[PDB]
Length: 37
Image (tube, rainbow, N blue to C red; front, side):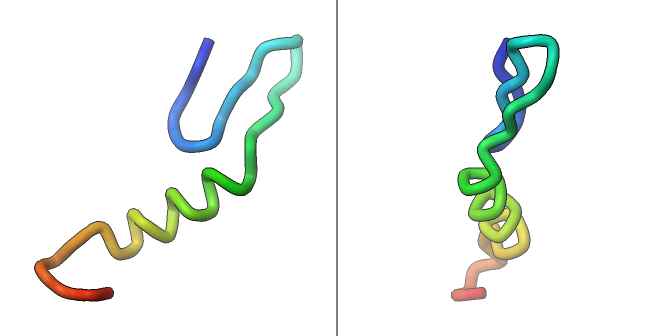
């Protein structure tokens, strides 16, 4: 049962990979916008 960015729950309790998700959220913060930020 995979999930969004850096999230993986599968043991009756999540185990979100906070690293992939922190960079994912940043990436989202600056997805594009035809720029560099």
